[PDB]
Amino acid sequence: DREAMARCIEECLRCAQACTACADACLSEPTVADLTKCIRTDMDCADVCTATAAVLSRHTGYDANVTRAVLQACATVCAACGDECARHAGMHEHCRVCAEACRSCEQACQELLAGL
Amino acid sequence: VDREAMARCIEECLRCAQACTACADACLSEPTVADLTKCIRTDMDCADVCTATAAVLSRHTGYDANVTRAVLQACATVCAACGDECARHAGMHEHCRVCAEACRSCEQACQELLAGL
Amino acid sequence: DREAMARCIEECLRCAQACTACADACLSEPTVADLTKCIRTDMDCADVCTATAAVLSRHTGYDANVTRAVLQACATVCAACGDECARHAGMHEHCRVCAEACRSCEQACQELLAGL
Amino acid sequence: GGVDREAMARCIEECLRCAQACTACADACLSEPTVADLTKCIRTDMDCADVCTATAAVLSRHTGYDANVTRAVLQACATVCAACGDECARHAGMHEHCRVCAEACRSCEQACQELLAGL
Image 1 (cartoon, chains in turn green, orange, brown, purple):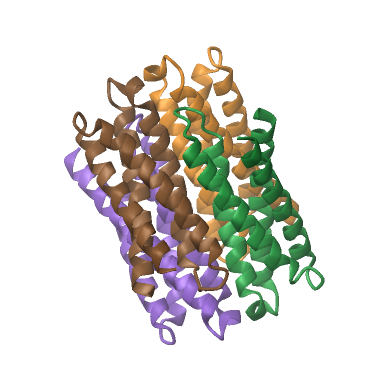
Image 2: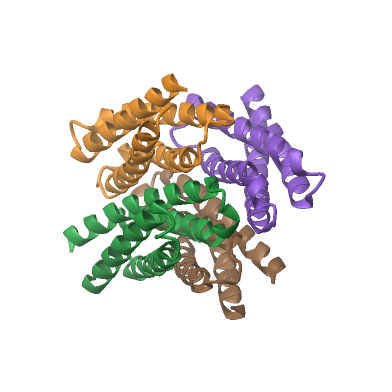
């Protein structure tokens, strides 16, 4: 599903950026001591999102085992990051926005996974 | 610099890394891959440096702006070199044309921030 | 175990570098057209090991499904990369070297996953 | 040449050691009760780690070598390792993780500067 693959890559790039924006904004909060789990998972999500986009971008010598394993990791980490950001969404707009982006990427990863 | 100029350059770096990864893969799949090895290698470098630059820019506050400048200059240099090599193959390979344009837009975005800092 | 954690992070960092080196050596071979899956899989492995090292560095024990997900992906891609390198190891010392690095990272990720 | 390839190997090794030192320091700072006073350290630790792994990767590649690219990357790595070392050194009195990170940054900075001088 070439449109599902392209959408997944796009969501990974959007999500990486939303996650790094969220990490930076949490680091700048006066209440940063209460946001350290959010910062950590934001960073985890950004790192896994860019790696996922990269693996999905390659078609030479395609191996479904690797593609599925990376997609699963990406879905799991986007879910964790979305849940953690959701805990602080009322207090912080950057967290609400990051959660949205994480849910969107999780869904695109699951859709792609189901289709492969 | 502005938050909107940062965000533009961070997006460009993320997109340029992806574009360079896609181009390197498309070149690897060509039957003429042996002719494309410098393109692939420079794609790989540009993706790595764009990846680092996106992350560094994300944490930019304005303090220790010499870090931001140094990383921007590395990104601009490799994007320009990657574009130059891709352009050598762009008449033959549309994938290289596409990559070259991604490299030019990231190069300009980095330069625009360098002027601002 | 923070010392096991550190050992696995080091494995991931060194495996990413090993894979990058191997991909470059394959790229420079006259027989590069026969080595394209090796190169691609080397790139995937480097990308996933790079993300894994970073995610492991931030592991706290909380939300450890994030850590499990990247270790599973990392073990899977390191196994695949080692398989493709091992196929070429008789002709190319650089592939032999890379397979050994992939196998050690594979094993370290598996061990850490068993401990969690 | 041979001396260059050996200095590149030494710098790659320092980059890998430095990346891990830096991520260990970021993690430790995030865990400190005084995390609010360590946010610049955490930011620069991460910048240094990201640039170090990229630099090791670029230096690993010999196909289609371009000295100008490699120099620009090395300059970035030297500059961030200097910044990271300086910021960690501010806190080294209070935090061993910061002292250890500063030492790794200094050693990586030196190895990058060696290649900038010798290539």
